[PDB]
Image (cartoon, rainbow, N blue to C red):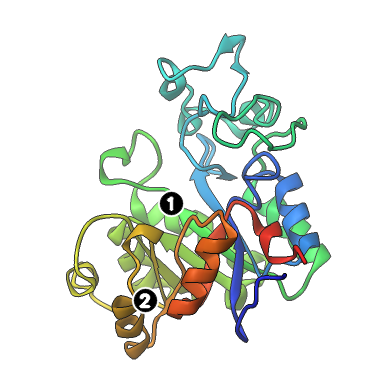
């Protein structure tokens, strides 16, 4: 029958619902909202003109993008189509929904573009006053000035949109980039942080990479252990792994004590 979840469990739609609909699109977010997810999960980058765009990558990815300025998007050229070198007026013209995704073959093919963060917010807020957000700052050290701004500007542009919409208390800012977490923690301490982890390491050695204890510890599912969950809980952290796409894996994790799930298939939770 249904997946049983504890009280206050956080069902997160990964990129809204990538398994079902083109990732990180208003269609995906609307579907996840209507399904009843707790949280819309999504990724943020910056255009040339300093608008916050919802996108997993700072470039148009070949898995999702049919063509840019007439060119077939492949592994060979995808990094040429750099969002940080493009004004949003140009970004918004490029379809990211009709191409078949080799890894999500049942995804619905519909016309879609990369939306502004502001549209995502204004869509979600119209539909729900209780929806939560988990937004990823897609920064890396090597990308500064090339793929996205410096840390302060990247974070400040995102935070400006959060404050404008008055969604601070329903917002978690997630990142792999410890620099973005440190900046957020010292400049905007009222916004909950999630620390994304994908490397080998003890929990202690991962946590020593930050100067503070974040709200959420968010590791690759393969890294999760009951011991680390219990340790994280004793520090007052919630544990929300990613990206978990089968019922049985979700059930195993729930039994170990996780506080939420990031999934491409949030419909798993509403299947009776």
Between marks 1 and 2 in the image, the one whose residue lies nearer the viewer: 2
Q: Residue at x 71, y 53 (%)?
A: 29
Mark identifier at residue 67: none
| First of labels 1, 2 by sequence position | 1
Q: Residue at x 33, y 81 (%)?
A: 232
Would residue 97 be found to the left or right of residue 258 on screen?
right
Q: Residues within 10 Å of mark 2 (few under 14, many from 20)?
A: many
Mark identifier at residue 154: 1
Q: Residues within 10 Å of mark 1 (few under 14, many from 20)?
A: many
Q: How many callouts does the rendering have?
A: 2
Give the percent coordinates (x, y) of residue 264: 59, 51
Q: Residue at x 43, y 71 (%)?
A: 193
Q: Is residue 220 visible from the viewing direction of this image?
A: no
Residue assigned mark 2 = 214
Label 2 sits on a secondary structure element that is: loop
Residue 4 lies in what quarter of the image?
A: bottom right
Give the percent coordinates (x, y) of residue 45: 49, 44
Residue 230 lies in what quarter of the image?
A: bottom left
């Amino acid at each position: 029958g249904m997946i049983q979840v504890p009280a206050s469990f956080d069902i997160q739609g990964h990129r809204g619902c990538r398994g079902l609909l083109p990732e990180n699109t208003i269609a995906a977010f609307t579907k996840a909202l209507l399904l009843g997810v707790t949280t819309l999960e999504f990724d943020l980058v910056i255009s040339k003109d300093n608008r916050v765009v919802v996108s997993h990558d700072t470039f148009f990815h070949h898995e999702i993008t049919m063509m840019v300025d007439g060119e077939d998007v492949t592994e060979a050229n995808e990094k040429n189509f750099n969002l940080y070198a493009m004004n949003y007026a140009d970004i918004k013209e490029i379809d990211v929904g009709m191409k078949t995704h080799p890894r999500f073959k049942s995804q619905k093919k519909v016309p879609a573009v990369k939306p502004l963060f502001r549209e995502l917010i204004e869509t979600a807020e119209k539909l729900s006053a209780k929806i939560q957000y988990n937004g990823e700052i897609k920064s890396t050290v090597e990308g500064d000035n090339i793929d996205h701004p410096n840390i302060a500007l990247f974070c400040d542009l995102v935070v400006a949109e959060i404050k404008k919409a008055h969604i601070t208390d329903r917002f978690t800012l997630q990142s792999f980039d410890v620099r973005a977490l440190e900046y957020m923690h010292s400049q905007y301490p009222d916004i909950k942080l999630s620390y994304l982890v994908e490397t080998k390491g003890t929990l202690k050695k991962q946590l020593e990479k930050l100067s503070f204890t974040p709200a959420v510890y968010s590791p690759d599912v393969t890294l999760v252990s009951k011991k680390d969950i219990d340790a994280a809980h004793k520090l007052g952290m919630r544990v929300i792994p990613w990206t978990v796409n089968t019922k049985e894996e979700i059930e195993t994790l729930i039994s170990l004590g996780v506080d939420g799930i990031i999934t491409d298939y949030p419909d798993l939770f509403f299947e009776k």
